[PDB]
Amino acid sequence: QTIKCVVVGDGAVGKTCLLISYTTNKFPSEYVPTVFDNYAVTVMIGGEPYTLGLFDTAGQEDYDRLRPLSYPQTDVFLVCFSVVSPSSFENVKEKWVPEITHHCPKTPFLLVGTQIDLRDDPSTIEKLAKNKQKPITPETAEKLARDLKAVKYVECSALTQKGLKNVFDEAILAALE
Amino acid sequence: EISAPQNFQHRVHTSFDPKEGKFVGLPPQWQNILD
Ligand SMILES: Nc1nc2c(ncn2[C@@H]2O[C@H](COP(=O)(O)OP(=O)(O)CP(=O)(O)O)[C@@H](O)[C@H]2O)c(=O)[nH]1
Ligand SMILES: [Cl-]
Ligand SMILES: [Mg+2]
Image (cartoon, rainbow over all chains, first blue to last red; front, side, top):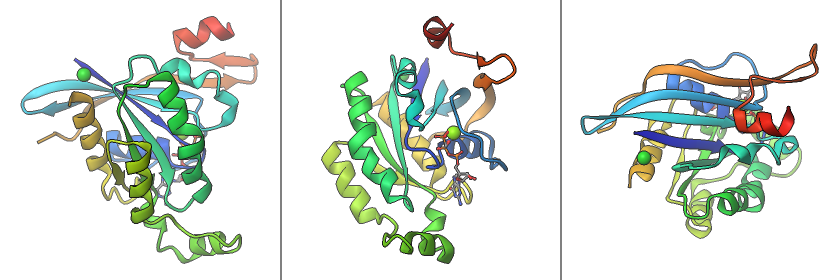
């Protein structure tokens, strides 16, 4: 059978890189915003192969009416934010969870923190500090996941691949559960 | 355990085509909204 996994979240959060890094073990060398892309991979769990269908959506608000047309029969959502983008974290509560709830009320989702390799980056810590803000800690991310009311919180880096496979392994388990 | 993913396929790629001035490579359910 086919697992339908839909990835949502603000622009610049890193959804395309997350997916290309995992499905291909290559990091995209360019930034190109998404309207819509559908990729497929095959995964095997306990001897049983599954097609994992991965829906890469646009985080730009311009696609608010169109994006959800892709949400029917979703098995699991990845609701993404960048651990170094507080505005993307706020929109999880304000835009993204409300959106996927409305369309798919009984579908499980994971809260996914992206770009964790940038937490200890001096010059992104600087960019944040010029507007008196700071990265999101796991402690804070995990409260939001509990409260909002996700399967769990996972985080990763598409660039280093730290925790990346785990994100999708938990997505797969959520869909099959 | 769960295997690493295999047999990567890029099935749909939607873009806006400025020469034609319309989205191209659309999912079918978007198509009957936009075309
Ligand atoms: N350092 C670092 N950079 C990342 C990571 N993931 C993505 N990026 C960078 O962040 C930018 C945004 O990545 P992209 O994957 O296009 O984000 P997106 O969420 O798909 C944007 P849209 O919603 O418009 O499709 C790119 O410049 C990319 O190189 C990461 O884990 N680490
Ligand atoms: Cl399934
Ligand atoms: Mg993208």
